[PDB]
Amino acid sequence: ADTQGYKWKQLLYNNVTPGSYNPDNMISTAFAYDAEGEKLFLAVPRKLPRVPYTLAEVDTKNSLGVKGKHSPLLNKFSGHKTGKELTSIYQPVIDDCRRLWVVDIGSVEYRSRGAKDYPSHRPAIVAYDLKQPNYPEVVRYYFPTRLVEKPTYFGGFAVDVANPKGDCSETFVYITNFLRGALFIYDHKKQDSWNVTHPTFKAERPTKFDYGGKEYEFKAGIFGITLGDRDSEGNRPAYYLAGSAIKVYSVNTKELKQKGGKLNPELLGNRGKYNDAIALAYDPKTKVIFFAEANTKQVSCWNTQKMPLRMKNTDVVYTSSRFVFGTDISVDSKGGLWFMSNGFPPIRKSEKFKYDFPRYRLMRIMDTQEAIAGTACDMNA
Image (cartoon, rainbow, N blue to C red; front, top):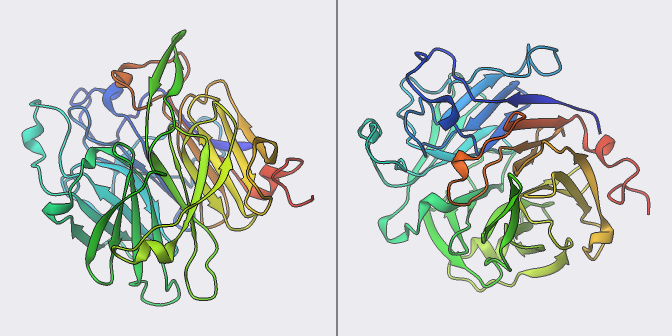
């Protein structure tokens, strides 16, 4: 229940001319922590002008639990020279073998000012090897034109590594898209990809978001996906949720991996009214799914082994009135639970939302077992 982590009023960059960008336009949407390397990676999408590095890193070693170091400066990704190697990303993910994956959207989202600096191209899945320096690029796949379907609305994604104790090439990437309600599946081994849609991906009803004493709304489809325990032969539950929804589902990865196959997802079932979350993360140690919530100012949990999922089978691992809009959550290599808020929900003009307290908040609970102690999510039942 005790946390260490970071707080930024604005995301400032190190080694970038002051005044060359507007700090309030630097809006981070997601992160990934590499525990072995003690590096934090942040996605800053090029949604507004003059973002110097869309993939930023911070070294956490002389930082994490130290007083006075709550606000580290962002740096260029060590795998980059110019910062143009990526156009705009929304989410970084670290896999079982320490490859940092990102989805390059391929274009910026503003006109002029100067968008000309970041030439448009097709969307791409890119991966870097953190085990080597300086993070060489090991995957780079462009989307075939016939498959592009509103790339600006990609959400969370998962990396399915079938052979973690091998060359790690038998890998799938499952990428959410919260507009339509669609999941883009990429087969790394076959160098093929396809689109999948389902009634279960779509939103249930608009989410309520409170800002400045008024109430705002948004209606998001499938937004987060996380992967369970691998069985006998490599297949696994892939738990997903829509952002504007309280139900949770799992479809098997074997149905997912088969191109043009029928999908049979399982409801399991819901988390209680007003508890919409856009991000969720499975902890293999405690078998718990953690949820970073849109409007409740809380991170919540459910033990996958306590069936079925009802509110009564859920609890709270974190509460802060300054935890406005949870946007990313994940478990690291050393079992640490990490969660982020940015006050930036998918609503018109939300980039311009401002807060008295620091907008950007990233926290770690050291180990998940400590987190769920004395909660409905713990081991005793």
